[PDB]
Image (cartoon, rainbow, N blue to C red):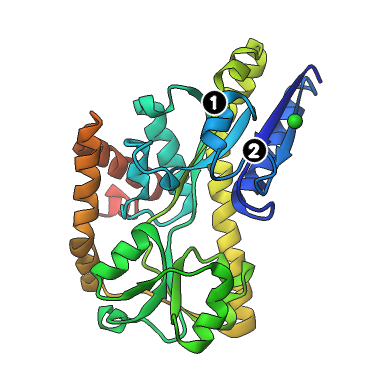
Amino acid sequence: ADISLSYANFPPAKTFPCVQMERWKQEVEKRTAGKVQVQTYPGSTLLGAKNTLRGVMQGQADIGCVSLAYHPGVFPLSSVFELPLGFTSSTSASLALWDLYTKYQPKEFKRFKVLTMFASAPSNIMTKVPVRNLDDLKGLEVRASGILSKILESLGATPVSMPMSATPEALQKGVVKGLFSSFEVLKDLNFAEICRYETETNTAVYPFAIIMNMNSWNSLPDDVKKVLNDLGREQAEWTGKYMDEHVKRSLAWAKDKYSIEMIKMSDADMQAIKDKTLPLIEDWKEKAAAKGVDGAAVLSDVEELRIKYEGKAENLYFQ
Ligand SMILES: [Cl-]
């Protein structure tokens, strides 16, 4: 190759942000006929959580993976995708996020080439004892942090912060009685052994951006830029599909091994959750306004994109 790019990624190799990174590498090397090579650095071996943004800006790495939620205030527009907005899959959230970015071109990313974006699967409640309604959450100790803790507090539950590593013992001791995370942990971290009741609240996702140093981007010939540009939407879709299938495999494994049960709360309970969490949306809108973003316009557009990628309404023909 004549062009060599380093790709920093903070989480462990086995996790979805790194898995998609490797697939992206494969497609870039193939589609450029070997003109570009990519060296990957999973698990914070080049840049980690503390220095991916600055590190990419400085060229310490050519490319890096950012979890937007870890940098409050830095992404006033794209952070909308941290909120409880009703997304029910990684695929739909990933594609909606990419579309929103492409539409708005927010200045929060002006220092970088944004190579792709994607989102986690939605956060759900996984517990030792079934949570079938909101009364079941009252006073319930659940491992959570950030916005998910805020949501639990608003629902009358008891969010507890603690390291993922300490959570198994904590669960067994009753220090927490479940966790608020995406379903892949049921298999990947064997949480299904302990938490065999999974309540699908589809609460929120975590959005990510793959960013590239502008000098590095500038250096690429036009044919290479086209390859990377074309991969933006493709990689958003690929990552979401990978993640949704990875969740599907987690759940099937857990059902086969421990007979886990999938639970949905009533429509009335789901509306109560919305009503109780509306302040988080209002907070975000004030934050957006303070940085010159039209928060209501963005939220409207997000729902339009959600329906585009998920819509459950029946065909007009049958209405
Ligand atoms: Cl390198």
The residue wearing badge 1 is 57
- Image point (21%, 66%), residue name: 271
- Image point (66%, 11%), residue name: 221
Whichever of labels 1 and 2 marks the residue nearer the N terminus, that label is 2
Residue 255: quarter of image: bottom right
At label 2, which amino acid type do we have?
A: Ala
Query: Residue 212: x and y, percent?
Result: 57, 27
- Image point (59%, 82%), residue name: 193
Q: Which of 86 and 140 is in front in this view?
A: 140
Under tag 1, what secondary structure? Answer: helix
Q: In this view, does 227 lie above or below 199?
A: above
Query: Residue 54: x and y, percent?
Result: 53, 31
Query: Residue 225: x and y, percent?
Result: 61, 18
Find out whether the residues at labels 1 and 2 contact each other: C-beta distance under 8 Å: no
- Image point (56%, 79%), residue name: 168
Q: Which of 98 and 43 is in front in this view?
A: 43
- CA gap between label 1 and label 2 equals 12 Å
